[PDB]
């Protein structure tokens, strides 16, 4: 028993992190097969970040201007190209520690583990959710760009995030591994607004099911509700509306606990209107939305990986 | 910026986890050099767990009764012994992935990362604190025994915890790597009481300093207090008393933020008596005590490892 915000084991990703230097800036890169992936703003000076013309800046660079280092081993760049907002550096050596992997573009509300790195070396690992407004609330300092987010399925590492920037509001933005930003952001040092952030309702419900599984049941009430009635209350409190796909995904948790999805919504509705009254759920005084239904099943069933 | 409950990268530990079978029970083991470490109750049946005579049970076992497996590689046990509550299995092969390591017995209030494992395979990693009553509030299912807790310093893995049991209250107990339990517990399936759990005050203060560093300043007040005056309030709310050693440890955080330790205590005193009034600190509606002063410095300065 117990419930924790646990990350994936990071071993398979630690072997893929390298340091990338171009001119004076040094960032992290991801080394898979004989290609290194890194944010394209590694080719910028501090002055270029206000209004960078990436095509014109990349022209002035040659293969021997990039220094890629894996610990003490040095890689030789034999070809470079720009794909959207990432740089792809072809190197002469294929990474012997390359795991089974794929590139995935996740949806808002999905969760992943971030391996925070500095100078190509791992600092720590934590779990987080892609917000509905396509930001993440991470923990990143100067030099962490190029750190990656990932999931593990079976023996396969699915890379889904590369860190590119901190917004003036202190939240974080980045791209998939094909270099397409999540959200309406651009890799430029300019004030950029993120939209309204909402709470991920299907995740909150998954967490209430986790709480029931672990013995927190005080919030279960006698009422029930309808989907339309619940969504009316949810939108007043800036919660994402629940759809039928969300009800389908919660099916297994409903089966295991014997609590129908709509009955759980009625409990949540009462928590939204009445608060928690100084009580806690799974050791928290706020409603938690960084666990997907799959995260709950995985943690409460003991799923392992390669 | 940002602040997260981040764990250490687990790669160096993933390469040390093995599966240990003796009779019908299968647990996790830790393979360093040519020795495997695992909980001694691997030699018990379900009936033996009520009142096990470990010496008499270990007599009936021979080297060829232990099956140790590292993925698909099979280790041959050539010698076994019992050190307190752990079994030490000598094997014919030395682990080629053995990192620089040491065994450490931590103190209550210190934090570490747990690599939760099942059948010798990693499931996830999370950070937690040793409670003042020598339990941990982890996330463990049947079969997780033998999972280890660890810290990383420089290039050295310090192992400090091996998981042995879940108490009837749903909290967890275990040993150091020499097999001495933390706390007054015994490896027997009997009702065992843990003492009163208190809040780790020096950790709460470290977290308030983290909050100031990241922009949460609303809780700073005009008052100050004395050490004796604060400890009187703290003990009424089941907080550990603050000593001079704790003030010394918080020194660097005081220097960085310009807020004296005693001034921060006065802010905390007001939070204890008046609550938080529906406000949050670093995204939490409760006072958090699972970050040590060192954890804050490490996260807010970007410390990396091998
Ligand atoms: C994340 C990261 O390392 N960096 N992000 C940068 C950026 C700035 C504005 C807009 C988009 C992206 C630049 C880069 C960076 C690296 C290192 C330092 O200090 C050593 C930086 O200081 C601000 C920035
Ligand atoms: C942690 C763990 O795996 N186990 N802890 C056990 C224990 C029980 C009572 C007192 C102290 C320690 C036994 C062991 C265990 C392994 C596997 C299963 O199911 C497959 C168990 O089921 C209860 C227990």
Image (spheres, coloured by chain):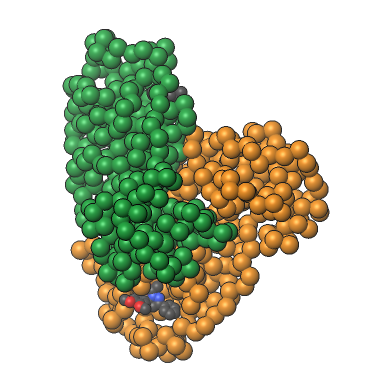
Chain colours: A green, B orange
Q: Residue at x 69, y 33 (%)?
A: B258
Q: Residue at x 62, y 73 (%)?
A: B195
Task: Give the quarter the ligand 1 occupies.
Answer: top left
Q: Quadrant of residue A13?
A: top left
Q: Residue at x 74, y 46 (%)?
A: B266
Residue A80 position (above or below residue B271)? above
Q: Nearer the viewer, residue B139 or B85?
A: B139
Q: Nearer the viewer, residue B287 or A58?
A: B287
The percent coordinates of residue A170 (x first, y second) are 47, 32
Query: In the rendered view, does B63 fall on the left or right side of B256?
Result: left
Query: In the rendered view, does A127 fall on the left or right side of B136?
Result: left
The percent coordinates of residue A6 (x first, y second) are 39, 54
Q: Quadrant of the C terminus of chain A?
A: bottom left
Residue A160 position (above or below residue A204)? above
Q: Residue at x 62, y 48 (%)?
A: B277
Q: Nearer the viewer, residue A57 or A164?
A: A164
Q: Nearer the viewer, residue B301 or B263?
A: B263
The percent coordinates of residue A64 (x first, y second) are 25, 17
Can you see residue A10?
no
The percent coordinates of residue B180 (x first, y second) are 53, 71
Q: Quadrant of residue A298?
A: bottom left
Q: Quadrant of the N terminus of chain A?
A: bottom left
Can you see residue A158?
yes
How many numbered marks are there? 0
Query: In the rendered view, does A151 fall on the left or right side of A2?
Result: left
């Amino acid at each position: 028993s117990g419930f924790r915000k646990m990350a994936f084991p990071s071993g398979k990703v630690e072997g893929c992190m390298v340091q990338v230097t171009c001119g004076t800036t040094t960032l992290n890169g991801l080394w898979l097969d004989d290609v290194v992936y890194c944010p394209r703003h590694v080719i910028c000076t501090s002055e270029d970040m206000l209004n960078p013309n990436y095509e014109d800046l990349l022209i002035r660079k040659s293969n021997h201007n990039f220094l890629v280092q894996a610990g003490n081993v040095q890689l030789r760049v034999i070809g470079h190209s720009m794909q959207n907002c990432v740089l792809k550096l072809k190197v002469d050596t294929a990474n012997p520690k390359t795991p089974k992997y794929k590139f995935v573009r996740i949806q808002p509300g999905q969760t992943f583990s971030v391996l925070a790195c500095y100078n190509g070396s791992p600092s720590g690992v934590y779990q987080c959710a892609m917000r509905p407004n396509f930001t993440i609330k991470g923990s990143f300092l100067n030099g962490s760009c190029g750190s990656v987010g990932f999931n593990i399925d079976y023996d396969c590492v699915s890379f889904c995030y590369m860190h590119h920037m901190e917004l003036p509001t202190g939240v974080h933005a980045g791209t998939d591994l094909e270099g397409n930003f999540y959200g309406p952001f651009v890799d430029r040092q300019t004030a950029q607004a993120a939209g309204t952030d909402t709470t991920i309702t299907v995740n909150v419900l998954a967490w209430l099911y986790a709480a029931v599984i672990n013995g927190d049941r005080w919030f279960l009430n006698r009422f029930t509700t309808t989907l339309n009635d619940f969504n009316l209350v949810a939108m007043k409190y800036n919660y994402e509306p629940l759809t039928q796909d969300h009800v389908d995904i919660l099916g297994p948790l409903s089966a295991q606990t014997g609590i129908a999805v709509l009955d759980m919504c009625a409990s949540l509705k009462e928590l939204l209107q009445n608060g928690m009254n100084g009580r806690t759920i799974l050791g928290s005084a706020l409603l938690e939305d960084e666990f997907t239904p799959f995260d709950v099943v995985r943690q409460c069933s003991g799923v392992t990986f390669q």
